Image (cartoon, grey):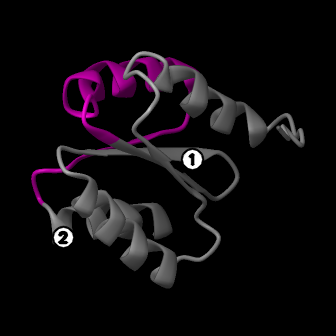
Amino acid sequence: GDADKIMEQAKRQDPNAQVYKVTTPDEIEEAVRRIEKYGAQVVLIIYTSSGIVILVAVRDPSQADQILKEAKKQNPSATFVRLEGVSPDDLRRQVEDVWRGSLEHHHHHH
């Protein structure tokens, strides 16, 4: 399905990129914990269907930009969030707010 396509769109461009798919907040704390080492460079959060969150990470920003450009053009509603200025442990709050937003709808404006 669409989740399996989107995770492979990262691997087809850079097979070294770490990608994981989670359906729960208890799975997110595992995904962020293994990404914390790798995503210390660059991270992307992807939000597909009614609550599935896919977490992707890379060691170069060009790989994230290229993968995102293909993934947007193939999947326009998949909602991409690029991470660089937030710490790899603080990334939890950004991923978890995207998990919660699927169940508990809020505007979350600046």
Q: Residue 62 occupies which quadrant of the picture?
A: bottom left
Taking the image as shown, residue 55 lies to the left or right of residue 46, namely left
**Amino acid type at mark 2:** Gln
Question: What residue range appears in magenta?
Answer: 15-42
Residue at 48% across / 83% down in the picture? 73
Of the residues under marks 2 and 1, which one precedes in the sequence?
A: 2
**Residue that sits furthest to the bottom in the current view:** 73
Q: Residue 15 occupies which quadrant of the picture?
A: bottom left
Distance from the alpha carbon under mark 2 to that under mark 1? 22 Å
SS class of the residue under badge 1?
Answer: strand
**Amino acid type at mark 1:** Ile
Taking the image as shown, residue 53 lies to the left or right of residue 66, namely right
Residue at 54% across / 37% down in the picture? 23
Question: x%, y% of residue 70?
Answer: 38, 78
Q: Report the residue marked by disc 1.
A: 52
Q: Is residue 107 above or below residue 7?
A: above
Question: x%, y% of residue 96?
Answer: 61, 27
Residue at 25% across / 24% down in the picture? 34
Q: Residue 89 occupies which quadrant of the picture?
A: top left
Q: Is there CB contact under 8 Å for labels 2 and 1?
A: no
Magenta-colored stretch includes residue 33: yes
Question: x%, y% of residue 5?
Answer: 37, 70
Q: Is residue 34 above or below residue 75?
A: above
Return the mark for residue 31: none
Q: Is residue 99 above or below residue 60?
A: above
Of 63 and 7, the residue lying toward us: 63
Q: Report the residue marked by disc 2.
A: 13
